[PDB]
Image (cartoon, rainbow over all chains, first blue to last red; front, side):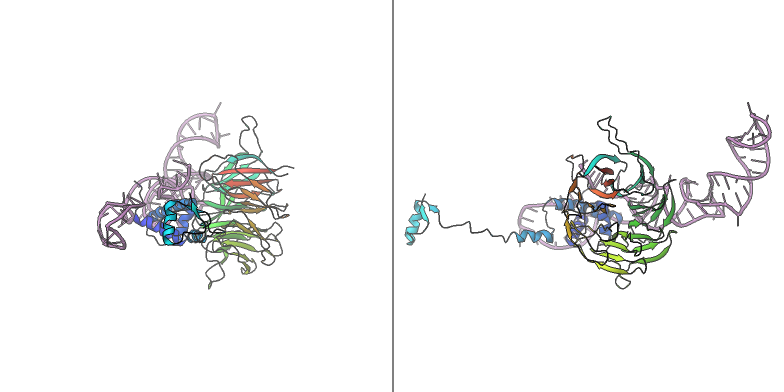
Length: 119
Length: 322
RNA sequence: UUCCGUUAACGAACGAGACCUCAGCCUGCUAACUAGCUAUGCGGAGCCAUCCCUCCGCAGCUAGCUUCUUAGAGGGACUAUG
């Protein structure tokens, strides 16, 4: 049974958020880096937290992930989320409808409506 | 014409971290690894075309065991046999390759050490460290100066230093240091002051290069962007683009080539034309997870052969055609 | 009741874990005549005998001695890699 507990998992994520750039995919260098940024009370705690951060970086370098909010990917998921096409794909020119739709449109008095025609 | 493949040698269990080659005692290659050993290879240059082109480029000759942790960088004496190596135990060691014993020991680096380098007269020794300090040593392994400290103490970096090399011009000895603080500095052995701060990269630096004639100052690192600089006075000539991480950098001894290890293959540019003309891939393409990077490279004295040491303790040798 | 996650709950407190002791690795560091190993000298005993060779004794300003012993500082393992 090698389930990591709350302290390790929480600290791993919370150190991934603060320094994504200075971590890497090797365990040993990550050990040293984690020794240069935080104050832990045992070597075994450090080895465990660094071991959980290294494959967290492997899967970060792979794809997306839960709660940790990386800056370089939260803006990149915003830079292309305020994304526009050349012109709006919702166009009012060829919008074909079925009997009851023009029946309601005749009810409203917009019986003649540019771009509407039966199926 | 181009670089060609002969074979691969396997003498290190863990990732090879440096190769050094001599100029006067030629057939003696030395490579360091994360195994605390320090192997020395002998070259009769065999290619056994008897067993499916039996794979061995040479036969291992001698391990200099004795370091207490990973050996990070090694270099050779410019006049004889001696070698100098730095490791994660905070020490530097001088080995004698004719008997396999250590001869001297540079105690004093308060934390891990990442780079070593000799000098022309071999009296000027530099050590770069995770201490966030550089220290100069004599041949006796005793102190004369130590450049570092924070802004008040001096001009030392704030992150760890990652690599140092000399300027091979004889009327102006200097030392160039790349750092994890994303800054390259140039120093002087005259006063251990800095000539210039070559403020470059946006990510951490892991490599610095000085031209064989001491004219321009290739440095690589995190972003994948290599920047070439001016040794005379700190000017950024042009930028090159590799994409992935960068670990090792080197110049051809006489031909005007710059080589790099960039985590998906070895990329050789040209400086005659600021454009890539050679990519070098691992021979065995097995679909295991992300393939062995090349972690270090070096040219021979004559530039006839380049050596690449990778993450699996495998070293693959590259010759030229004609 | 370790964690992922689900979710009228959200945020926390103990217990588990962490932690401390001992044992396991270190020809790397610090050393050690209240621990020793090595070499050299003298002493004995064998012997192709004169030296060499082997086995013990003994004494030191022998050690570019600390492998063995002791005990300190650290390193090492994290399921790290496939």
